[PDB]
Image (spheres, coloured by chain):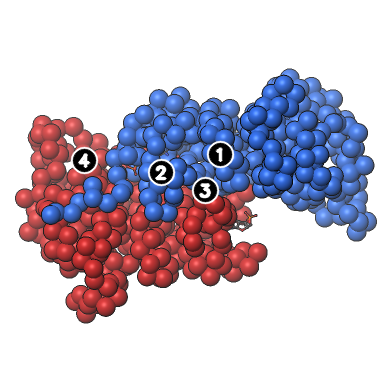
Chain colours: A red, B blue
Amino acid sequence: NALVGRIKGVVKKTRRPEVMGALCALPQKYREPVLVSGTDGVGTKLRLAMDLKRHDTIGIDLVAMCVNDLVVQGAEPLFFLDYYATGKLDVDTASAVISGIAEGCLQSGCSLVGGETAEMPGMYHGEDYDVAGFCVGVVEKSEIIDGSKVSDGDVLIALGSSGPHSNGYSLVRKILEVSGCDPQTTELDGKPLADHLLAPTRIYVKSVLELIEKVDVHAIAHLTGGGFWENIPRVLPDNTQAVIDESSWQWPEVFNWLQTAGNVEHHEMYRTFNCGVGMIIALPAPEVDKALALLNANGENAWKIGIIKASDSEQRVVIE
Amino acid sequence: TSLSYKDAGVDIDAGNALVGRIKGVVKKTRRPEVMGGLGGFGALCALPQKYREPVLVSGTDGVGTKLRLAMDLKRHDTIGIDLVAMCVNDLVVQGAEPLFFLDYYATGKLDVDTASAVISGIAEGCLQSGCSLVGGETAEMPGMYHGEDYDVAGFCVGVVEKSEIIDGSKVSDGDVLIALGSSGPHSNGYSLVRKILEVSGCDPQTTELDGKPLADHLLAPTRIYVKSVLELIEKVDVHAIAHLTGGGFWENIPRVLPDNTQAVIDESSWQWPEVFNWLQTAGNVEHHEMYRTFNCGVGMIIALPAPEVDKALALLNANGENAWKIGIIKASDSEQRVVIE
Ligand SMILES: Nc1ncnc2c1ncn2[C@@H]1O[C@H](COP(=O)(O)O)[C@@H](O)[C@H]1O
Ligand SMILES: Nc1ncnc2c1ncn2[C@@H]1O[C@H](COP(=O)(O)O)[C@@H](O)[C@H]1O
């Protein structure tokens, strides 16, 4: 009861004109609208945000995981829901989470149109909580990005990440335990290590939506669980191989610290962590200069990261 | 020593292995509108052609307290049906046709057997609802979920024509109320069920009720009313639909009724199913509390004009529903919204 009164303003402030047990009409511009949907959790980053007592941006990570997966197919995020499960409801912690959710929905252009708070005393111990996200997007049927147009000679453009995002934090913590350092006191390029690790996931919705209107995009890969190895081949057609130019960008320093402190090997770094790349965009080579100029001039760190070449190799991704 | 994800406790390919097993039961729920398959970054589904001004109806749910009792008695096949039922039954309240469903599964270490049986119930509920299971998420949080505990959440999206949204405005003095029988407590009132089971010292497995174990009455999967309600809206003027969930008769009936209207419930029009008499006896529960906590055999109530009752009862009973006239609507002169007599 004390929660719904505090979150009524954050639901109303995200309301789109299409919003009217949650009612939402389709945007008027779509002729053959196709609905794009997905659900997600934050992951182990919750328990790291709990240990540091900072839940401010954890709701941004939840929305970002959703909406970045929708926009891969060219979908425009429409509305969002959450399922907040906890043992004993901390009104202050839940309000901070939902506020971060509202902030992520505003960056995505979608409305927080409802949700539920459930209390399970025997299941969750302490003040722990698990939040499930749900987003629905709309894409024009003729403009769905399926990756079939990915051909030999396409160039890969990377979008820089704000940090580890919401994947790999089970290894992050395990590295913190063996190293035995305080993330709040361990300074790292002028900031504490905790700030590098708790940085919310970058939301790529608006910049990728602008890119699709202006250049011909063949495929987009959101680097989440599994990193480069698992997520890049999901958008590759048969008999294609992505060759990442490792020298084309420097790792953000947080990933250097994680490798040294955990003695993490090369292949494992690119599986568990994004290593500074939030998304990879496959597009024809003549479109690259237009895309790089658009993305970099509109709040993104974009650079040429690799190429797609014809290859029947079973190793679909090469990082050399 | 080179640390890795293997040294921790999350296995990304555990959910990938679960998706590897459940691809069969998921594919069987696929609708013609569904495009693509599992594994992609997002689930694709077109709008049904019938809607010229389609409005999307969405909801999230969790079976909650009933999930606790399902683990205790070590039965997790029907709890997926309960998850879908609470979603899809709420969609049709406003006239929405269910389109697709997603689920969020969280636990400590993933038991692929336990999860696949839960998903199989979710897929079965989607078959009954006419919607598709088009995606989900499987998260492993070893420190947060102790023992074999797991938490599942459901999300659903339905479609309704803009000009046909049911908002209770068409409810008028004289509308006859038709009840749809429930299959049991459905998914609400299970904190009181657990309490009654404790104060009475009752093991619901070694306790027989009408020849069946009491655990079969308590954990009966929620009845899904989607196909019956959609046909009702298509063939009969439906003014309001009450979904008796948390809060029983007192809370859920006025939620769909317009202001200055009152629902009069004929208590003699039905007898409580035996599971509710047991819960009332074993807990010494006031009947007013039973009408607040449990649905008491009535899962849904439909408001419609009086001349259309016989046709509606004919349709509902034809789909295997337990339908009967439960009451009427009358103008509330600033009175009580629900009256059971
Ligand atoms: N965690 C949450 N996030 C957003 N909205 C919520 C949440 N929990 C409840 N609500 C909203 O609060 C109202 C009452 O929800 P309930 O308590 O489930 O009846 C509805 O409008 C819900 O959508
Ligand atoms: N519990 C689940 N039930 C149904 N589908 C799922 C579940 N978990 C994951 N999926 C689907 O499996 C695919 C793999 O998702 P990801 O784990 O993000 O690679 C996606 O299409 C998901 O929607």
**Alpha-carbon neighbours of circle 3 within 10 Å: few (<14), some, or many (≥20)?**
some
Q: For disc 3, does the CB lie below 8 Å from ligand 1? A: no
Dot 4 falls on which chain?
A
Instruction: State whether discs 3 and 1 lie on one chain.
Output: no
Whether residue A55 is visible, yes or no, is yes
Of badges 3 and 4, nearer the viewer stands 4
The spot of residue B152 in percent (x, y) is: 50, 44
Dot 3 falls on which chain?
A
* Quadrant, the N terminus of chain B: bottom left
Q: Secondary structure at mark 2?
A: strand
The spot of residue B58 in percent (x, y) is: 56, 46
Q: Amino acid at mark 1?
A: Asp
Q: For disc 2, does the CB lie below 8 Å from ligand 2? A: yes
* Residue at the far front in the pictured view: B201
Is A66 located above or below residue B131 in the figure?
Answer: below
Of badges 3 and 1, nearer the viewer stands 1
- The numbered disc on residue A233 is 4
- The numbered disc on residue B137 is 2
Q: Secondary structure at mark 4?
A: helix
Q: How many marks?
A: 4
- The numbered disc on residue A26 is 3
